[PDB]
């Protein structure tokens, strides 16, 4: 009967911090071939979204590509879709930042010759109040998933039309991405998509199905270049989709200029379905997966999927404390820097979402993406006057201590081993502790043997000046892996503190539990210096007992595929050119240095691999009753 309207869109994005070859590959593998083929089919209509950095990379490297986009826009083949310039997850940044973020990209769209009216929701993380924000930015529609609607209570059958939604008395139009099309396109043969769309036709001329997904899926994703281009999937699809009398191709704006949204509906906090898995704590994510698989295993996932639920994106801040700290620190800086445009631009760049979470691969686990966020938090803050302060930054209920001078910002957590969790260099714009601890993930456990022997999961978070207590006969390999016997209770327990001039005095009354609790007291005087910091230690035991006290210092060493190593040293240097640079650790007394890379499990189609998140340096000093020494970190 009536034709079925079809909306085709792509979303192109490269997170800040990506290697140059990555942009080049995505452009050659996807961005360019895709538009060249679109140019060949005058009747094809595409709704495309480009992230700000991407458009900036293109203007600098591939200017001609922009002339092609202007042309296609001019011939009615492209509707430019926007969002937050630097791909922030809108719901996770200040409302003020949402405005400027979107307008920066609206300005760019405008320069391609198109007044953007729609927004691609980054990671489709929805919150009711985004309505107000999108509305203030002049946006008339946002792109979400069918799953957001199913979660609200509607059945898939009533999701082939866009809907209105309101908040604060403001209303905006919402289009749902048909999950099926995300799997049919472009991975399955063309006929599979044509058959599906044709079966959707009804007596309702306004019915519409929506496809909108990653542009990189058409060429970059493993295997897609061969399938989409070498084997002609795109050319065959564009020909089929434009030569079908039951399928009416149109852009989002064209649809709204002809059909009114079906009605009013309210959406919960959600994202696309797959995200319901990743955003759950590892244990629960595993259960979620078992549940989904067992439903499919009993051929009943299809009729019951509308009731399946999982986590929400913001909970990555719970799953990864390092992401939460990163996030809250940028929120802190965004506020203090809001009236300074030059400074503010840096904080807006720090809101690029990728490094804040982890799906099946990458994200927060890629040091280069993480350092880029930190790099920007630091550059924005550098415009502010240094000022020490006590406050609960990551909201765990126990204040942090921020000590800072003209060249550094150190964040101490008295509650957790009185350690330094953040040592940011204002000169290098690097956080020396921009590392991650080794954690189990629901998708772990197949993994090869060569890697299993190097796998280990931490019980300790990782910071700087982490006080240990091990047996003289303890081995590096036992320590490296988490097998060793930690005699003390100072690594993850609270420390008393006293503020001083340019630093803090920390001390803890604990004990060295071996054969009997032997009460101990660790003291550390941390003071910021112009090129780092210095810590004067004074360990004390209540009763004699041969042992080894160790001060651990984790470092965001990224470009140094370091390996386990133990050596004798009073002072040693570290040279990490592409990461934290050059630094020196000086002791006033020699010690046994234990070094090892922090390895994290990374899954790819090329099997399992390892990502070095940083390196741990532990300076061991023997102790029986009294121990006194000084450690100095120096930035070169
Ligand atoms: C992370 C990604 O999730 C969503 O993507 C899903 C695709 O739409 C699905 O079709 C499916 O793709 C798999 C193929 O079916 C399969 O045959 C094989 O080729 O592997 C594909 C990938 O596993 O599953 C995808 C989820 O795994 C979503 O639509 C997409 O926008 C999301 N991409 C964002 C995430 C990151 C990571 O930080 C960014 O690099 C992207 O630019 C974002 O758009
Ligand atoms: Ca806290």
Image (cartoon, rainbow, N blue to C red):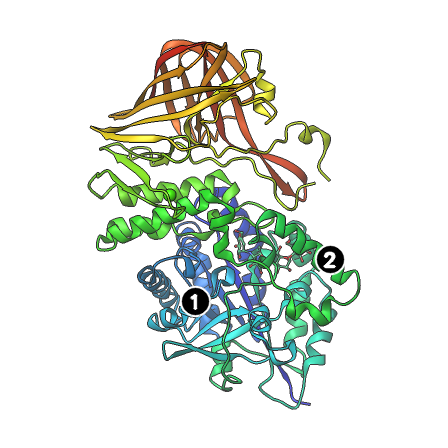
Tag 1 residue: 70
Residue 399 position, x and y percent, is 33, 42
Above or below, 426 against 249 in this view is above
Above or below, 369 against 143 in this view is above
Q: Nearer the viewer, residue 393 or 546?
A: 546
User: Closer to the observer: label 1 or label 2?
Assistant: 2
Q: Nearer the viewer, residue 198 or 428?
A: 428
As drawn, the label of residue 28 is: none
* Mark 1 crowdedness (10 Å alpha carbons): few <14, some 14-19, many ≥20: some
Tell me how far mark 1 sits from mark 2, CA to CA: 46 Å
Residue 446 position, x and y percent, is 73, 40
Residue 497 position, x and y percent, is 30, 31
Hey, which quadrant is residue 51 in on the image?
A: bottom left
Q: Nearer the viewer, residue 507 or 55?
A: 507
Which residue is at a point 40% across and 33% down the rendered structure image? Answer: 494
Q: Secondary structure at mark 2?
A: helix
Please give left or right for residue 240 compared with residue 12 in the image: right
* Mark 2 crowdedness (10 Å alpha carbons): few <14, some 14-19, many ≥20: few
Residue 57 position, x and y percent, is 42, 51
Which residue is at a point 42% across and 15% down the rendered structure image? Answer: 541
Ligand 2 sits in quadrant: top left
Above or below, 583 against 280 in this view is above
Q: Secondary structure at mark 1?
A: helix
Tag 2 residue: 293
Work out whether residue 635 can be spotted: no
Give the quarter of the figure containing the N terminus. Answer: bottom right
Which residue is at a point 37% across and 62% down the rendered structure image? Answer: 105
Please give left or right for residue 52 compared with residue 528 in the image: right
């Amino acid at each position: 009967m009536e034709r079925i309207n079809f909306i085709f869109g792509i979303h192109n994005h490269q997170p800040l911090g990506n290697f140059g070859w990555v942009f080049e590959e995505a452009y050659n593998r996807s961005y360019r071939p895709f538009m060249e083929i679109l140019e060949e089919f005058p009747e094809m209509k595409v709704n495309v979204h480009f992230s700000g950095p991407l458009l900036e990379w293109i203007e600098e490297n591939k200017p001609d590509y922009l002339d092609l986009l202007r042309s296609l826009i001019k011939r009615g083949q492209l509707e430019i879709v926007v969002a937050g310039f630097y791909e922030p997850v809108l719901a996770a940044i200040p409302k003020e930042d949402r405005l400027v973020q979107i307008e920066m990209l609206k300005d760019y769209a405008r320069k391609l010759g198109y007044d953007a009216k729609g927004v691609w929701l980054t990671e489709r993380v929805w919150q009711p109040e985004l309505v107000k924000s999108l509305r203030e930015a002049g946006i008339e529609y946002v792109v979400v998933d069918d799953y957001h609607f199913m979660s609200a209570g509607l059945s898939k059958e009533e999701l082939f039309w866009p809907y209105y939604t309101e908040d604060g008395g403001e209303v905006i139009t919402v289009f749902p991405i048909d999950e099926k099309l995300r799997y049919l396109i472009p991975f399955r043969p063309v006929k599979k998509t044509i058959e599906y769309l044709e079966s959707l036709t009804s007596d309702d001329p306004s019915k519409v199905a929506v496809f909108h997904d990653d542009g990189e899926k058409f060429g970059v994703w493993p295997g897609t270049y061969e399938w989409v281009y070498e084997k002609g999937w795109l050319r065959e699809f564009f020909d089929a989709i434009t030569s079908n009398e039951k399928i009416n191709l149109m852009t989002y704006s064209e649809y709204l200029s002809k059909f009114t949204p079906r009605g009013l509906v309210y959406l919960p906090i959600a994202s696309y379905f797959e995200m319901s898995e990743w955003s759950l704590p590892a244990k629960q994510a595993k259960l979620f997966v078992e549940f989904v698989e067992q439903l499919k295993e009993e051929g009943k996932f299809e009729k019951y999927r509308v009731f399946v639920r999982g986590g929400i994106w913001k909970n990555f801040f719970f799953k990864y404390p390092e992401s939460n700290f990163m996030h809250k620190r940028m929120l802190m800086v965004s506020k203090a820097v809001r009236d300074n445009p030059e400074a503010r631009k840096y904080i807006l760049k720090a809101q690029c979402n990728d490094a804040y979470w982890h799906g099946v691969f990458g994200g927060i686990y890629l040091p280069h993406l993480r350092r880029t966020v930190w790099e920007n938090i630091i550059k924005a803050q550098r415009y502010l006057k240094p000022e020490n302060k006590i406050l609960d930054v990551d909201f765990d209920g126990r204040a942090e201590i921020m000590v800072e001078n003209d060249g550094f910002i150190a964040t101490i957590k008295p509650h957790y081993g009185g350690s330094i969790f953040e040592l940011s260099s204002k000169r290098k714009a690097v956080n020396y502790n921009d590392v991650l601890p080794r954690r189990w993930e629901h998708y772990h456990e197949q993994i090869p043997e060569e890697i299993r022997r190097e796998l280990a999961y931490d019980w300790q978070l990782r910071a700087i000046l982490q006080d240990h207590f091990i047996k003289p006969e303890e081995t590096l390999d036992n320590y490296r892996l988490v097998k060793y016997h930690e005699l003390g209770d100072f690594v993850n327990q609270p420390y008393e503190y006293e503020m001083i001039e340019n630093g803090v005095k920390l001390w803890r009354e604990g004990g060295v539990y071996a054969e009997e609790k032997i009460p101990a007291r660790v003291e550390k005087k941390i003071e910021l210096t112009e090129d780092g910091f210095i810590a004067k230690y004074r360990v004390l035991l209540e009763k004699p007992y041969k042992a080894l006290f160790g001060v651990e210092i984790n470092l965001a060493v990224h470009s140094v595929m370091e390996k386990p190593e133990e050596f004798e040293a009073k002072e040693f240097e570290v040279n990490d050119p592409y990461g934290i640079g050059k630094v020196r650790i000086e002791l006033d007394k020699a010690a046994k240095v234990w070094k090892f890379p922090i390895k994290t499990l990374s899954q790819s189609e090329a099997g399992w691999d390892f990502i070095q998140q940083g390196v741990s340096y532990t300076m061991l000093f023997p102790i029986e009753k009294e121990l006194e020494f000084t450690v100095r970190f120096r930035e070169l």
